[PDB]
Amino acid sequence: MQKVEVFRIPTASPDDISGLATLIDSGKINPAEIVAILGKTEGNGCVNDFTRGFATQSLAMYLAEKLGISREEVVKKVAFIMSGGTEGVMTPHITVFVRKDVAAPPGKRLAVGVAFTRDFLPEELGRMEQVNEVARAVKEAMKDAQIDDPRDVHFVQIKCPLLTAERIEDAKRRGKDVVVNDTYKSMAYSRGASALGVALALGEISADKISNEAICHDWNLYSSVASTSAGVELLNDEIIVVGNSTNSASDLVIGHSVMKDAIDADAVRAALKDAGIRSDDEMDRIVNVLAKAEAASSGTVRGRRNTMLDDSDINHTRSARAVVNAVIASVVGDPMVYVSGGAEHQGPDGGGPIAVIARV
Amino acid sequence: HMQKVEVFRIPTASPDDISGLATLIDSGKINPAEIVAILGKTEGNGCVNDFTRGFATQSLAMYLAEKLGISREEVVKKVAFIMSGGTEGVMTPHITVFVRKDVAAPAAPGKRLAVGVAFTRDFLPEELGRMEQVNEVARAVKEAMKDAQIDDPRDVHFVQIKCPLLTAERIEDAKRRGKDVVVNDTYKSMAYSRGASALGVALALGEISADKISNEAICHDWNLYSSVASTSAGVELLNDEIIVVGNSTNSASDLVIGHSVMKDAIDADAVRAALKDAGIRSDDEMDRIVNVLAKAEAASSGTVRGRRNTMLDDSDINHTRSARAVVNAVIASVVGDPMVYVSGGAEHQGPDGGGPIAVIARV
Amino acid sequence: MQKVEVFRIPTASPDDISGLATLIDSGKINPAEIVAILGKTEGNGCVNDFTRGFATQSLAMYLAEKLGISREEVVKKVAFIMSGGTEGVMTPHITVFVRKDVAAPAAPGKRLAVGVAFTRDFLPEELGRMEQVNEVARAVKEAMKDAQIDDPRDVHFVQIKCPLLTAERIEDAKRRGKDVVVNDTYKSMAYSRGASALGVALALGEISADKISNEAICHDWNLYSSVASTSAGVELLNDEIIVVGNSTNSASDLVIGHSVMKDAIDADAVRAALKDAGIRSDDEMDRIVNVLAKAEAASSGTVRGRRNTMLDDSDINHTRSARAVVNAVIASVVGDPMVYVSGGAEHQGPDGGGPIAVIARV
Amino acid sequence: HMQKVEVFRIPTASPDDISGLATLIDSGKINPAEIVAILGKTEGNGCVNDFTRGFATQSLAMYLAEKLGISREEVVKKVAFIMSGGTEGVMTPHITVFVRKDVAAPAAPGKRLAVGVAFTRDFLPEELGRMEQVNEVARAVKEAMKDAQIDDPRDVHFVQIKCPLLTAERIEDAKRRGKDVVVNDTYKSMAYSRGASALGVALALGEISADKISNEAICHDWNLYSSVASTSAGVELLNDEIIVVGNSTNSASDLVIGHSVMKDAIDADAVRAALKDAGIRSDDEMDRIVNVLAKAEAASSGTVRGRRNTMLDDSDINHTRSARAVVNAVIASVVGDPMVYVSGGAEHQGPDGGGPIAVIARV
Ligand SMILES: [Ca+2]
Ligand SMILES: [Ca+2]
Ligand SMILES: [Ca+2]
Ligand SMILES: [Ca+2]
């Protein structure tokens, strides 16, 4: 039997491992059983965010020394997905996923799987090469989680690469053309291609509907559970599949809904209910809320104009994260929840998936 | 005669967009001679170097001057123009136009919306954030209450103020004249102007006694605050402009105002309390909203309900910008509409980390 | 006979008309003879910069009341080109171009001449495409005639204001069944600037028409003008053109010269521009009326092989950084940060560089 | 006691890039045991929430610990790590590595490059920007002068310091402990830490007499400044780290250091004067530059040579970011290379609006 435990840990800085160390030193976490850490780090969440790599380096160092292995082996063994940007009231934190085998005694309970893709050349980001390799890795992660029914996947969290000026120019020197000649926009193509990879692997969209031309163009194509995030600190995709399976002894469950837009508090309440939280009094059973946020391509929300796509000072994914975190925070009474910005092919245009991990 | 207040919340396409107001004037719904105040959300950064505020006022004053056949200077002496910059997150730029009609009709039964306007003298740079600004604002708030025909401060539900700030040029001029300003920082000067102005509201309304207010308490003693003050700072003016909004027995308005106080930036309960205080008791009655007006800020503790955030540590985005995005998103999620008024920096306006929130609603 | 006088006026804010009013009230400027005003306004110089429109509105309202005509007529008569972004030490200011008819003879040789022309408004789906290139080229030739300049070699600076795309305008284009050149408001500024600059190069013979296509715009950096200076704004829907050069039929006591900065730190090009304008030593720097230059981040992400972060910085857009850098370089050569520097130099000088002109007293 | 200093300016591809240093170590050009200090330009925002500084130090400490077979803790006690954030404009990220070893050499002709290092104790938040930091820094500067074998302060040409700052959480902790900090503003706290640290340099070197320094003068009396101090603040440390750079008769280095003082942000003449003071007398000798190190800042007057700028009014971009872009561009245009060290915020470092500038050059 598979047992998943999940710990939401406040952090004081990107390199703060003290909260995790406390759980390890007390015996609550066996570090050998950590399979994934999903972080909100307090950089800008865009191209030049180095808090993501700083956080991964610090955690890999700490765990490597606790486990007596190399940092390189830790990163091959544990998924480190650091989502930058803690705008508004969003509280920096890490979510640690622990998976234990115990033979013990109902229904379906939380299950997790992890998979990594190969490194991508710069000219492969945002194109079918990334779509198809991610799709394979998602199936790989589903099996690792022992989930056979794609309907039982409630959240697929991915970290994916981006283009820097340096990588674009290197591609230029090698005679290769990149999907887009813009560092910030490259994040959208990488996020969206990865998300279409989830939809492809999960059967949400048929392969004949996906092409290079549809990536970041056909917003009718999206996954209802995909959550993708981009960073300078890696060259491949890291996959975490989270769902429920009948062969689990976890005392946790995951549910989800889809925010129709950035202010869709109803979808937050629907996600809570799908995870078994039916009243405000049961709010303390939340382990974490995980959601995608984005600026709608129309430049409006419910017929009302906003400046997210016109604001040259603050990039739109920063604003979307602040908004959606505030909406969730106002429903659950806690701003320490995971919100990642840029939801290309993840929920509808201007919306995004939202999942809740809760105590049973 | 009898006062009837009508309020129009008008979407804008840019700071200088007067088209929505012009449509209401051209259709006969607004007599421009009866406009008494315009409260705007303009899409600049809402901080020191926000010129969308002055651009919006200039555009409105030009337009109204030409419609009325008077000079822009006379319009500005007659009509309050309070432009609150910063439309972060999903917050929708718009203006709220306050029209006051004299009508030979009976007052409505009970108390209905009433509005009053008053302007203070200009302040010297060295007076911002100090008792001179507190006491002059308090005097003007009482004048605006009289203008609104509100004698009981308990019937005042929102006092909206525009106040000045310090630029580097004004600080340096003060230094040459041998004067010390309250703070040698342009962005922080907004907080002192906002806070002194808010304490002036609290003093005028009896929310705080005069003996508790001193220069040393301004922007320091957060136990002192008004539950209805809403203050906003700008480079585009040198005085304080005051709009008092409340209810009066001597009003024929088909509108009312209610309010509550957000205890913190994510206090959706306070939004629902303000709606209820304005007579909106269910989600179906939210179509009676004319506007929601709220103050937002980063708490001095650097936390919300024990959870850290970076608003006070973020050197890229100033904290009033972040607070506005948050509180607008919270309100928008309750009412289903991000076109509501949210202003940042709530010194002495509600508790530390919170702020007053009012609702103007149709009866 | 034409005489051009040029006044560089410090401003205290985008709406500050006091310095211009002082020159009018002192008798130094007849407002009826103003033909163009080129401003540096202290907004962010990107998409959501409303200081540009605030400055034009304030200047048009002031001049309309001084002249006893409508604001609409002022805007039809006078070019208002407000370049946002005053980063670093760059000092906000306006440069006012006055053109007088004089009976004096022709000054021996060539002296400053200015011409102005406007294009029609463009639909959003036209920005960054050949329609903008070709309409700009037509207007540049008209402005050359207005300036009485027949030889393109005597054109030393072609300053343009051009439109941009906002989310709402993109949505309008979509609603009308049209696709825009790019679905990014900030990037739309580059396409508008670049198409406009290629229009200058076409009109002046710097590039042949058969080399220009929609695909080349903002892609083939071998195609550029050595005198074009283009600037984009939400506050207008057309292109406004100011051609500045020298003409034999000018009685101006000023001349214009120029060079091309090869990169953002090319102080040699600043000195070369000064020398081309007759300023041969540091002591003659007092003859400067203004220096006008284009600045940009190179697509390579480097300057002389050294990496910089301008194209990777998600907090500060690259045209803001380039303006701060090039203004500082010029300021250090001429001893004055109140010079005109505009960012985003697509097809204006080489990739990573831009034209630089000097207006100087003879 | 003859000492030889070698200095290596190394381009970096990211804050954590150690590859250039590893190349010099692997080729035998640098014995890692002889590294005494690393001075970095890291590509974060250079303000409060810049974590590239700590990322760079952590990466360098890890790498050196593994190369030397010691713990990271010992590396940090052994090697000064001063990471100056902010690579605005064309400023190129890089590190400058200082190697120092004893050598059996004869007396050099004249004086040659010398370096000394010293660390202060950790400071309480309430000690930053006050005499406790001034006096402790002065003590450490004198210690570093001894480490460098420089007895005459006129032979000190650059004193580079990393110092702490205040975050919201540290301010709130101080408040909970009943303590008042020098300023209740995270960004402004950097200026007080930088300025107090610079005054400590001036005190140690005899540039200013002790009786002129008090808490009230810190960040207020701009007549008081050091001509060689260069201070930089960061969240990643709680003490001050000091690198003294000068020339000594007891040096066998093939390098020298010279300096001047930029009177304002566009003072290219001072750049050429610093080059000349380092023995570089013509453009043809420019290839002898190892690095140029300079301080930059926005003048409190809000102007440069009487011309207004917006650095102190700009609520979007903090003034130290703008000053760094400007001064780096000025230097780059003189020397033809933007990979030079420029640090922003020059409180008590050169005049108001200016700052020291040093050149390390091959003989
Ligand atoms: Ca989506
Ligand atoms: Ca408050
Ligand atoms: Ca160019
Ligand atoms: Ca200084």
Image (cartoon, coloured by chain):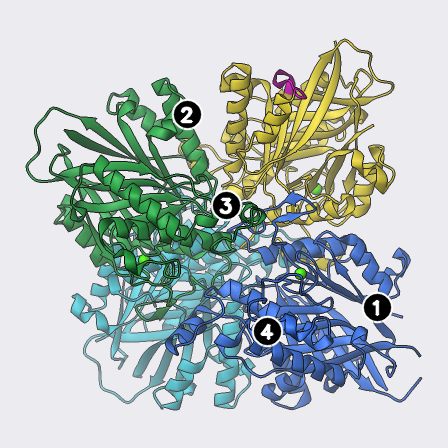
Chain colours: A blue, B yellow, C green, D cyan
In the image, taking residue A360 as reference, residue A213 lies left or right, namely left
Taking depth in this image into account, of D271 and B23 the one nearest to the observer is B23
Q: Residue furthest right?
A: A105
- The answer for how far apart the CA atoms under marks 1 and 2 are is 64 Å
Which residue sits at x=34%, y=70%? Answer: C306
Chain identifier of the residue bearing label 1 in the image: A
Dividing the picture into quarters, in which one does residue A156 lie? bottom right
Amino acid tagged 1: Ala
Which quadrant of the render holds ligand 1? bottom right
Q: Residue at x 65, y 42 (%)?
A: B220
Q: Residues within 10 Å of mark 4 (few under 14, many from 20)?
A: many
The amino acid at mark 3 is: Asn
What percent of the width, then of the height, locates residue C171? Answer: 57, 48
- Residue D331 placement: quadrant: bottom left
Q: Residues at marks 2 and 3, common chain?
A: yes
Q: Seen in the image, is A181 located left or right of residue C209?
A: right
Q: Quadrant of the C terminus of chain A?
A: bottom right
Q: If you read the primary sequence from the N terminus, does the residue marked by circle 2 or circle 3 appear first?
A: 3
Q: Residue at x 52, y 76 (%)?
A: A124
Name the side, left or right, on which A60 lies relative to B334.
left
Instruction: Name the kind of residue labelled 4 in the image.
Output: Cys
Mark 4–mark 3 distance (CA, rounded to whole Å): 31 Å
Q: Which mark is residue A160?
A: 4
